[PDB]
Image (cartoon, coloured by chain):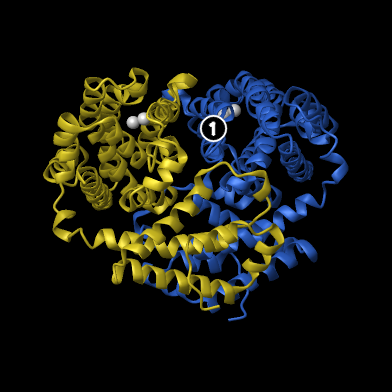
Chain colours: A blue, B yellow
């Protein structure tokens, strides 16, 4: 009743039994108040730019996307969480995305060539203009200074994304046109080890986490606010059909940048003697994501633009959202690792 | 304002521009009224059992799932449809599922053995008890009487499901445990032609539709109410994490029954001389879905039950939902084809 919403409040919702959820869902006054509380939190996070409200907002979103991405537990199979959780997510997402678009000007997303092959050259040039494409965390800190403790902290941040990449792709390809769908589908099958459990990418990522004891409590204690924002952006864009073309740009940039970044991590990892089985994940992606990137530009981005060049604007927006949010993440990471 | 909701009203929503959607989403009085209208429609459909309200309800749900499953058009990329469409779907789904569970008694879903391999034998026995496992449309009408016009009408009904089976699987495997995920993932890759566009299952299904001119207008004109219900059930169960274990039973029954059904269709199709390229889809699935069924029981159902035997109840519910809804669909189909 004219209340404040935070993560603990949403945990309380998720503890409700199925009848309690049905009663909440029927109460549009309670639901109005929840929405008003979300708008209040959004203003604190992004208008007043309170860092504590910003982290709270991303903690709330992260809890909701956990429900979207995780196998449901038996205890909650009967609980209708969509009317409330989708309202909270729409309000908080709308504020998160509006803040991203505040950093993107019309001049950045409008002068692209309106054909697919040409658009790819333009986008790669635009990516190369952005500092996140050659960030000193990878280019300078990793090869010269990174210790085991640095990599442990870094890997904690990377759990925002890599542990769910297969399901990000599965969400993205829903309803996709044939050429784009086939490329995303092959990418997904690659993520699924092409049928071999040992080669499933989330499994090999978990082995890197094990190698440095990046345990669940360490992650929760050490996850940076911008790491939470990065993970929430990826989830937000993957799970709505309407964000598909942004996602194409967002995960296109991801595939494109992984090989240079991971080569630097892998080389340092070996230099300082860290567990060889620990970088199977990264070593693999050096060649795998080069293929994924080429396939992504040629078979997702270029056909999409050729089908309807208007989507070039959405793809460029998604690319810049990934670049901008990556820059803030890496700057925050490098700042915490320096100190 | 104390209004009646139908498909045309939801089409009106989907015609709103992004600002109009934002204003609707902020208006919890308008949203309360929409929910009340959905509850009214549910009562007409399932309490009063008005056949016209039942078809309207499934027309509304079908339009919403279209948004969930289809590539978003450029014109609607900025429209936040989730707060309203997810409320409508939760209310109408809750009524659809409650009507299904009305036909399922506790004695049917409770005496299963609480281990995976044993559970599979029990479930196959339970399926074999149900009339939909050997329905006369397939067993008697198809081999002895079905004409080209009969198959054209039948294929129109089958568009409720087969054109989206790859994305049903993609939705289902989100967050799934490793053994179950790997099996669903291989099934999905099979649906995606194992990377060969000509072998993509939705593509070969569309060729069967072409062979008999099952065009979009024919489908809309001829789709039976129970065909709409079947398609909506599949969508409902696939898209919520909490319905995962029901989905495991629902699409498990689907995989299990397809080979005997399709063998009968294929044999008749050839007998009456219909286009040979028209049944590439069905001919393939005779052997493919036998493998999919075996894999599904051994690698999805049995590991799930061994992980937590409590889910055996959900899987049995989903299996009976598929069996019951299939029976009503096939009885309605055979009745219309007889007349
Ligand atoms: Fe990968
Ligand atoms: Fe990749
Ligand atoms: Fe298939
Ligand atoms: Fe299959």
- Residue B125 visible? The answer is yes
Residue B274, by quadrant, is top left
> Residue farthest to the bottom?
A1
- Residue A150 coordinates in the image, percent (x, y): 69, 37
Q: For residue A72, say whether it is visible.
A: no
Q: Where is residue A155 shown, x and y percent of the image?
A: 62, 38
The location of residue A199, given as percent across then percent down, is 47, 24
Report the residue at 17% width, 43% height from top: B127
Residue ID for mark 1 = A205
Q: Is residue B264 above or below residue A160?
A: above
**Image point (26%, 33%), residue name:** B258
The C terminus of chain A: image quadrant: top right
User: Whereabouts is ligand 2, in terms of quadrant?
Assistant: top right
10 Å neighbourhood of mark 1: few (<14), some, or many (≥20)? many
Which residue in the rendered view is the most extreme toward the right?
A107
Residue B42: image x %, image y %? 37, 68
| Figure quadrant of the N terminus of chain A | bottom right
Letter of the chain that mark 1 sits on in the rendering: A
């Amino acid at each position: 009743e004219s209340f404040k919403i935070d993560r603990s409040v949403v945990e309380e919702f998720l503890a409700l039994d199925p009848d309690a959820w049905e009663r909440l869902n029927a109460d549009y006054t309670a639901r109005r108040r929840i929405g008003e509380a979300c708008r209040a939190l959004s203003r604190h996070a992004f208008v007043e730019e309170d860092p504590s409200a910003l982290e709270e907002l991303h903690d709330v979103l992260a809890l909701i996307y956990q429900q979207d991405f995780s196998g449901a537990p038996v205890e909650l199979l009967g609980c209708e969480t969509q009317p409330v959780l989708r309202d909270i997510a729409a309000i908080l997402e709308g504020a998160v995305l509006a803040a991203e678009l505040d950093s993107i000007s019309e001049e950045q997303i409008s002068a692209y060539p309106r054909s697919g092959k040409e658009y790819v050259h333009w986008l790669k040039r635009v990516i190369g203009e952005h500092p996140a494409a050659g960030h000193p965390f990878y280019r300078d800190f990793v090869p010269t200074r990174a210790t085991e403790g640095d990599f442990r902290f870094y890997l904690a941040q990377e759990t925002n994304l890599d542990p769910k990449f297969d399901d990000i792709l599965a969400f993205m390809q829903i309803g996709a046109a044939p050429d784009e769908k086939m490329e995303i589908a092959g990418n997904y099958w690659d993520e699924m080890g092409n049928g071999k459990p040992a080669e499933v990418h989330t499994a090999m990522f978990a082995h890197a986490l094990d190698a440095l004891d990046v345990n669940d409590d360490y992650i929760r204690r050490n996850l940076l606010p911008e790491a939470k924002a990065s993970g929430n952006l990826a989830s937000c864009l993957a799970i709505s059909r309407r964000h598909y073309y942004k996602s194409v740009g967002f995960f296109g940039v991801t595939e494109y940048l992984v090989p240079r970044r991971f080569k630097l991590v892998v080389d340092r990892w070996a230099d300082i003697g860290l567990p060889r089985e620990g970088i199977a994940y990264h070593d693999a992606h050096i060649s795998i994501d080069a293929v994924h990137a080429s396939g992504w530009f040629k078979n997702v981005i270029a056909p999409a633009v050729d089908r309807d060049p208007r989507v070039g604007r959405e793809i460029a927006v998604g690319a810049l959202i990934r670049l901008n949010s990556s820059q803030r993440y890496l700057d925050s990471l490098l700042m915490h690792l320096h100190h």
